[PDB]
Image (tube, helix red, strand yellow):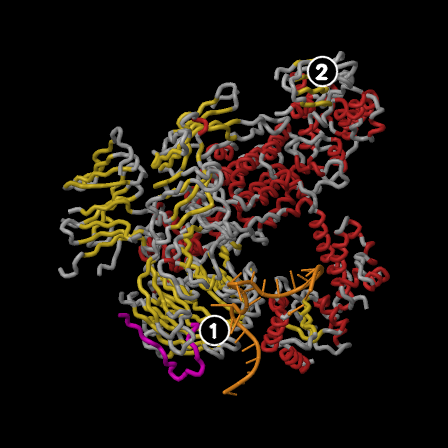
Amino acid sequence: RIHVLKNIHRESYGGVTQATFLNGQPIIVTSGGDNSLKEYVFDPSLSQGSGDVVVQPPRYLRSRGGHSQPPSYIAFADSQSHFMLSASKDRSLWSFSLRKDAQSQEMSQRLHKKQDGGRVGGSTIKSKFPEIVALAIENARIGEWENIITAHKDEKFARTWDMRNKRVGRWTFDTTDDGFVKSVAMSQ
Amino acid sequence: GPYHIKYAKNGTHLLITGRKGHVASMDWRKGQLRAELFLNETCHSATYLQNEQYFA
Amino acid sequence: DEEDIALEFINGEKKDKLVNMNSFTSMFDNIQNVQMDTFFDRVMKVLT
Amino acid sequence: SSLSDQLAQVASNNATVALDRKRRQKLHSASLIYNSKTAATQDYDFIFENASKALEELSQIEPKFAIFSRTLFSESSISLDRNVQTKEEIKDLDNAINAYLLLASSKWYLAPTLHATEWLVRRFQIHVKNTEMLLLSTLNYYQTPVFKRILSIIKLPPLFNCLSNFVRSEKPPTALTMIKLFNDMDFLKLYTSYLDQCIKHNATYTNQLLFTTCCFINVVAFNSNNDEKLNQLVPILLEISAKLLASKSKDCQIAAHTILVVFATALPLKKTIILAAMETILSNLDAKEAKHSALLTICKLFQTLKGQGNVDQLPSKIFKLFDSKFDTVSILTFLDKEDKPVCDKFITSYTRSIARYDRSKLNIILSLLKKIRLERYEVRLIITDLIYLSEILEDKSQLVELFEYFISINEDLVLKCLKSLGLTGELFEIR
Amino acid sequence: DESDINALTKILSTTYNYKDTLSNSKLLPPKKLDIVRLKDANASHPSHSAIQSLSFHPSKPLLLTGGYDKTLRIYHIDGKTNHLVTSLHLVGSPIQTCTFYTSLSNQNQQNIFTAGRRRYMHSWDLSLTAKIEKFSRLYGHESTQRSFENFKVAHLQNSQTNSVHGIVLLQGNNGWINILHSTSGLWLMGCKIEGVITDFCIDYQPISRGKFRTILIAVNAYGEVWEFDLNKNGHVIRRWKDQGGVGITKIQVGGGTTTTCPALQISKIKQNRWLAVGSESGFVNLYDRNNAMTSSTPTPVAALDQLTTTISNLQFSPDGQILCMASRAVKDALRLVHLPSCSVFSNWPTSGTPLGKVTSVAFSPSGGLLAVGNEQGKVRLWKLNHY
Amino acid sequence: NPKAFPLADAALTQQILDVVQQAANLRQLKKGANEATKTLNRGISEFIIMAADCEPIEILLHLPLLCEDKNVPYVFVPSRVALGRACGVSRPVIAASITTNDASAIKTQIYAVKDKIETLL
Amino acid sequence: DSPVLQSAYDPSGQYLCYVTVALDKQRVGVQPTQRATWNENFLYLEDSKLKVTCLKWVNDTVAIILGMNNGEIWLYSVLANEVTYKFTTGNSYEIKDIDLMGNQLWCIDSSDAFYQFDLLQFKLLQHFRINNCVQLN
Amino acid sequence: SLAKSPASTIQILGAEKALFRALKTKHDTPKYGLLYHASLVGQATGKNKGKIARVLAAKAAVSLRYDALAEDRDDSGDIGLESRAKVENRLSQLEGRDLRTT
RNA sequence: UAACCUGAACAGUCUCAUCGUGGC
């Protein structure tokens, strides 16, 4: 048994639904019911004499994907109707392209560093943010600082995001009255 | 660009020219290149003179 | 009394030696022309 | 990619072809005996004739080199150039070189093998073409100047990357460097394939088995604190344990015993894996030192076994196989040793398998559990299946005297098991 | 090539996991814990002081916290929402030790005994107004007991009837332990050790059906340990010496019924297997009382040295497989040492565990659940997934 | 061990190890046999504590021989493990010299323990 | 948030059944809604991860059916303190809802399956599943 | 008189003029002395021959004052042999390390 | 009666050490 790629697709959406080798090629395309299509490639062997017994494990290559759950919120990122921000119940914020579907990219949730230098809390096993109730994007100062302000399900602070970097921001705005965020806005 | 090829008169050295600017003189049968110069105007052709030591 | 049986089962457990990073680093010095059964009991002395 | 990268690839392909005098000198001065200024002036006839002398010496020491005198050391091979024949002739002579190297891996302490493989280094360029097999064959000799010499002249493979600060150095690689070399996974797959060819062609020698087992148990020791690396590592070293147990050498069998005992005490393996491991241990047990190591190995592998199901009766096939390899006198004697091994859970499983599968040898289980002391759950399960033995078959003096032993010690416990199932007056009326 | 001694190869080619699965383990794996963090137990209602003592209920899901702000709070704990059951503020009486007592006869009393640096000790009778009584009479022995701080509650049998009653045990000045009734407050007996009494613990051992025996185990500062049989008159049965150990702060037993893992039913009383003597340098000797009740200079099975300042808590988990060393002197000084292997778990606590300055610790009797109270006034709560 | 003269009883060894612990907190002791003999040579030791627990005791019983030349008090305690705990290191300590000081906070405790030592000489 | 995880009245609103956590294990208790007509004993779920997903009062030995998260419907009498009968499906899927009409119990599964049980016969009568209904709760 | 000297003195015992010039001006003292010609220090190489000159002087102080101060001594080399085993495996564990990165 | 020691008893207005720089 060469290798096992575990959790290559979600079991709840069907597992790996079709996997096929492109023939003559060391690349295999998988697709699952979680709205995802991946490719995995076999690199050539690392031993220069044996080869057939030292099989390097398959690594990841390109993939396309979308939301695995129906989206819960929708906004347009700019006045040109090129990108649109889209948040789903599977707790991901995607930025989908209306012009060319290769440009669709998941906004990353990799947090910044704390401003003073203290530790940030949270679980070690990183999971995605609670699913997005509302959002408000105003790209007047885009690239300059935080640009999207978003409000999640049953939590008392609103995160920010940067659409230029396509990532989370440094700030989570609290409500200061122990109430969940019911709306967000931002000025132009 | 498209590469004009040229060999030395004994087959030891190879001289390639890109159409864009990339001229490389090399020992194609070892792995030794001895000139890789990017002359950013459109080059057309090259040749060795009497050696791998000079090329036009 | 299944809790009492479970407590006597976890009570009849004896202290063992665990493998460290460096429980076997000092064997290369004396793997020279000794026999393999002497190596086996030299390992078993480390494990016990 | 870039042009200098693609040209480095074509240099690495054309590494061995001498395309002028300076490359021929730099490429022919790589000797294993002489220094560069002598080695560059030597011929093929000179190094061939004294390598043929050394192969005659090596062949009268060990007579399996005569066919290498027929093919690899013949006089057609003076003019045989390596990089002028096709891939099929290349793979023919490269498994010829692999055969010579894993035959002469054992002989590396005596100078005829140095002067003989000098000709493989200088004619067939095996320091740069067949280099992985050369390193893997002489890996044992790493404190020695012959491994210093092959490291000085070698071109190092990408799997052997940590030896790159010990090439052209005056000090030998250290043991921690050897464990860092073995700690990779692709290197572990490479070395286990090398051992598979060794075990297949019957060339495993005891210095190699010692070095291999030392580096393996140090890999397990280094990875003893990350379970995902141990779990990546289990079907490699247990596979090589199966392939060492599936051979005839007592030395390689107890090498596999060492690997199995360290690996089972490093992580708690599955019960069925431990049982199949003891089946593979017993299925080829022929020696005596192998029997000593096999009994100690099966005892520790059953000791390192937790949960509901540690001390069941081991099944009928494996129990009668363990009987055919180890009878009663062997088990009783080994328990009577004053060094006191820890044989608790295995001896409990053994006596319960006797009570389910033999039903004649109960005086011996009285004597052996008189010898060694057990725990409360062990003797509780023993007396429960003795109670079931009394209720299935008629209760004679051997079962009666067993219950006299279980009355003479810990009578409250046998009362507790009878009250959990049965009655004391009813059991005394039974027997 | 082929169509379809190989037992190991076949079992490896079929298996994919290679370790014990979930519940066919029944005893803890060493060196790697499995411990999730729950909601902080006193997060619902904050504490106004360092949390000086902490005890779970023997049966109910209740956690009693208490500290120098002279109030004691009971929390219904669960995973999500640890709420506050009730809360009683004793004015002018800062509390230092607070214990759920639950008798063995009817298991229906549910007293809370609490005490601080005072010449009295309160006893709240749990009734879900609040009826509390005050013990303030040492019946002739007030000179040798000037502060009710260090008490422990235990069970005692009459040994001519099979009638048990609770005793509280007060650690006094000279070497004295004053044992007195937990309902009437009558001074029953006293046990004097020779030196500076620093700590003590209670061991029980069964004798027959329905009879057990209570042993008080009291340690000098120097390291010498007295064991008093006190189901008879409080007379010494064993006197031994701790190997090493010069400033001795805390002794504990474990592996059976301690005062912190209490038995609900008299037939469920067990003999303790382990005994840990933790010292001022952070050294914790560990003795195995399945063989170390005979030697009279017994050697420890291991001396742990992992945390370097003064041992102020050391508690055994109810199964008796983890010991918890803890120090209130520096921050984050808590270790969980697995035993019998006597090896500290290396994956918890990490550098980011919000342990704080650990000034109390408690183990749940059923759930497998740590509560750790620090000097900021926070009980943090963890669940061990082996249980 | 028989040849470990004056050995302390429990009360004297408890107060010896108490003054060792507070001298270790005041950084006023030299722990180890070689450092004890260095303080013996330099004449800056108040008294020497040794352990009657080392398996060769002859690695110890040489600093008595230059204690009785400089008439500095010396004493034996029964446990090298407990002496190491008192000195406040993680290793067993075989001998320890409490060094001299005249502005020391624990000067009175050092003097009381050394008088109790030189009563039994 | 509330500690009471599940709760339901009997018909006529005379008793309240309620599932709360008790130090990592679920417990099911019944209280009378007026004392003028405590109840200190609970059903204890003995596993730390087995939990009640739904509950329904039956209507005459009075009982609760507790739909668990391991493909079981426990049937638990309240005057006594044991689960009297353990209905089980063939699976391990948590069950999202139950109901009953008379003696005929019906239940839905996390694999969107319908099961029918008979309280008078203690048997799984029917098992089926229907198209385009795929997230039933 | 050699037995009642500390192990640091037994380390530097031969190198008195280098020692006292390197103390009377504030320089770095020698590390070998007369003990440099021991076979173990010969086996060491680098700065760890200073290191095992130190550990060899420590174990040599142990063995030397055992020999001078024992009365039930047996002339059989037992304490010196266990001390030599300690020094040899210490020399092994600091010749096994290497300052290179592999 | 006291003195002294001692329990987690310096340190957010951060405390302390050491080497320097400029003017305690």
On the question of residue E148 being in view, the answer is yes
Q: Give the range drawn in magenta.
A: E129-150
Q: Which residue is drawn at 66% across and 35% down?
A: D161
The residue carrying mark 2 is D84
Q: Where is residue E261 in the image (x, y as percent from the top left)?
A: 40, 62
The residue carrying mark 1 is E237
- CA–CA distance between discs 2 and 1? 94 Å
On the question of residue D427 being in view, the answer is no
Q: Which residue is drawn at 72% across and 21% down?
A: B30
Closest to the camera, between mark 2 and mark 1, is: 2
Name the quadrant of the N terminus of chain F.
bottom right
Observer-nearest residue: D75 or D132?
D132
Are the two marked residues, 2 and 1, in contact with CB atoms closer than 8 angstroms? no
- Chain holding disc 1: E
Name the quadrant of the C terminus of chain F.
bottom right
E226 sits left or right of E109 in the view: right
* Pointer 1 local density, CA inside 10 Å: few below 14, some 14–19, many at least 20: few
Seen from this angle, which residue lies furthest top? B9
